[PDB]
Image 1 (cartoon, rainbow over the protein chains, first blue to last red):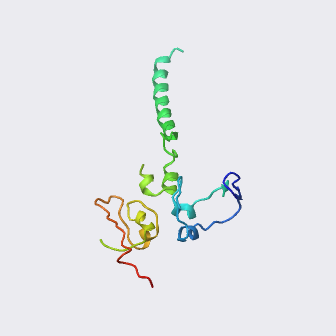
Image 2 (cartoon, rainbow over the protein chains, first blue to last red):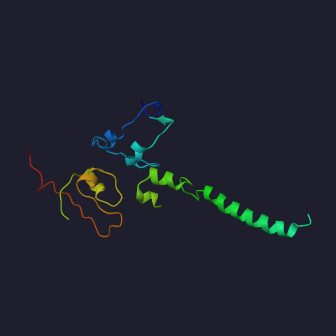
Image 3 (spheres, each protein chain N blue to C red):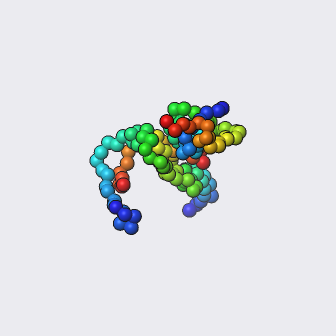
Length: 50
Length: 49
Length: 49
């Protein structure tokens, strides 16, 4: 979607492998703010939104 | 209220201990007041801060 | 320490960076002192084929 109508998808009830996001070189910017990128496989979350 | 002088000292010491324990719940501007949450969420360059 | 990398990977030659050549090719410590030097070498380290 466009940025004025940005699409929000709920992520819930899943096990997430973020290591395929870290190890992929396709992303020009992969920058996390309140959490380390390599600790994402060790934590549990709710209210995940893309 | 006959024994208020001793009870005042006991209450002051217990209140000072309770305040010192309560001060651990404050984050003092950090992201969390729990050290384990910071050590499990962040890399050491920003977890150091 | 001399090497040749890409143009977008020059941000990863730094302390406290997350990145690819930082993890598996060349890592700088968090207490690193010194200078990193980078200049474009498209005229020397590139071929048309």
